[PDB]
Image (cartoon, rainbow, N blue to C red; front, side, top):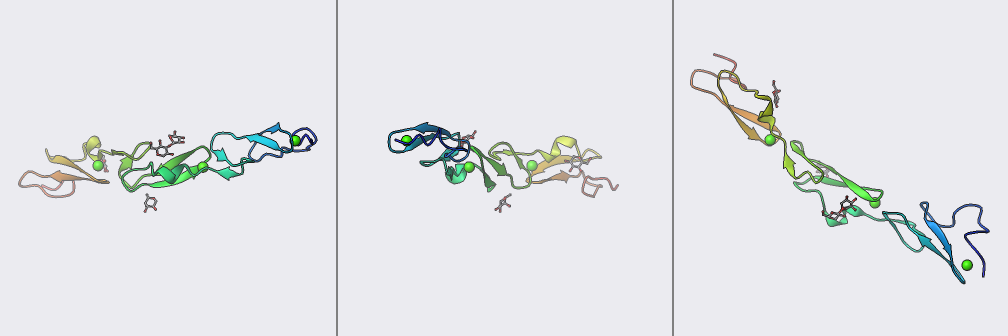
Length: 118
Ligand SMILES: *[C@@H]1O[C@H](CO)[C@@H](O)[C@H](O[C@@H]2OC[C@@H](O)[C@H](O)[C@H]2O)[C@H]1O
Ligand SMILES: *[C@@H]1O[C@H](CO)[C@@H](O)[C@H](O)[C@H]1O
Ligand SMILES: *[C@@H]1O[C@@H](C)[C@@H](O)[C@@H](O)[C@@H]1O
Ligand SMILES: [Ca+2]
Ligand SMILES: [Ca+2]
Ligand SMILES: [Ca+2]
């Protein structure tokens, strides 16, 4: 048998996989996110569709990241930002939290996006 893990100048496994010599061939212990007989395959962690609310899943090494639609947040984009948190309405306007925006319900006699015009 040839020791592919010892006689090699560089790792015969891909992606820093750990070479384990066997009789007639060799084995590769793959790090997280890699698969295949030589760890050559990058696992697509986005195949399970983890991102919610029409977010876009980007495949990463041993994981993923979600690009949220505007107005959403969280690991899976499962939360909605509350644009009313900053108290945008003035003149005692009531703030309604929408997706990626707020709406100020103004008391009669006031207009404007945040009820700033008497
Ligand atoms: C397939 O969908 C799952 C829904 O939650 C998701 O967990 C899976 O994600 C992975 O799990 C969480 C993250 O921390 C890991 O890095 C990732 O492998 C997804 O693949
Ligand atoms: C927080 O308040 C500001 C105005 O002060 C507004 O621009 C933001 O949209 C709101 O979320
Ligand atoms: C991925 O990103 C999200 C935010 C949406 O714009 C999708 O349409 C896109 O494919
Ligand atoms: Ca061998
Ligand atoms: Ca991946
Ligand atoms: Ca919102």
